[PDB]
Image (cartoon, coloured by chain):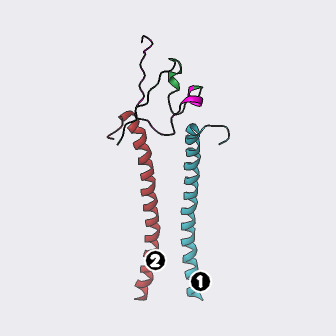
Chain colours: A red, B cyan, C green
Amino acid sequence: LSRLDPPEAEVQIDRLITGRLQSLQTYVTQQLIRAAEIRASANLAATKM
Amino acid sequence: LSRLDPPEAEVQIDRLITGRLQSLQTYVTQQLIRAAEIRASANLAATKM
Amino acid sequence: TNVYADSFVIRGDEVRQIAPGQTGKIADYNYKLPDDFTGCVIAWNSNNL
């Protein structure tokens, strides 16, 4: 942003943005799966108690 | 790779790369879900044994 | 950190071949720029001198 022009900063920022969005989405989905597994284990522990 | 120049080959290779990456990621996520289901079924079978 | 000022004198038509990603005679036999950016390119008409 300091050393480029908006007409092309648009393109480069778009590349960085789509990459970071893909990474955040991957993180969220893997956390969802792992939290489902943890929920199943906590259900097991609840019935065992 | 054969019939084009690196300065232009960059973008075509990038398109193929992002597509194949998306496909591999889809495969990995669906395999994760199916393996969680199989784990639940093997837990049921262990308890039944 | 440093500044490299390279200087020469070429044709007025071949002045377009001073660029990374262009082909011809000047680009392929005498001078070239890598698959990266340069600071800036400047060219002035000086056939009067």
Which mark is on residue A40?
A: 2
Quadrant of the rendered image containing residue A8: top left
Q: Is residue B26 above or below residue A4?
A: below
Residue bearing mark 1: B45
* Neighbourhood count class around disc 2 (C-alpha, 10 Å): few under 14, some 14–19, many 20 upward: few
Q: Is residue A47 above or below residue B25?
A: below
Q: Helix or strand or loop: what does disc 1 sit on?
A: helix
The magenta stretch is C26-49
- x%, y% of residue B15? 56, 44
Q: Chain of mark 2?
A: A
**Residue at 56% in and 54% down:** B21
Nearest the viewer among C15 and A29 is C15
In this view, the residue farthest toward the right is B2
Residue C40 belongs to magenta span: yes
Nearest the viewer among A48 and B1 is B1
Q: Quadrant of the N terminus of chain B?
A: top right
Nearest the viewer among A38 and B1 is B1
Q: Helix or strand or loop: what does disc 2 sit on?
A: helix
- x%, y% of residue B19? 57, 49
Q: Is residue A21 above or below residue C21?
A: below
